[PDB]
Image (tube, rainbow, N blue to C red; front, side):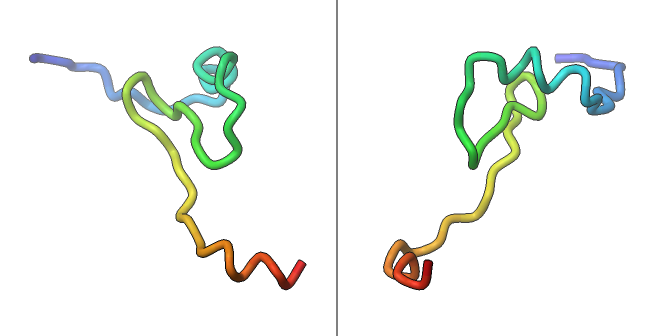
Length: 48
């Protein structure tokens, strides 16, 4: 497919994209793209 827009990521778009998403380690930074956080083993959770 052909797209000519830069798809510059704006903050005003994130709220509408993530209105139904309540995750803390994933947000819809784009339409089909995501911003994620790397996982860690829960065995390290004992330090809290």
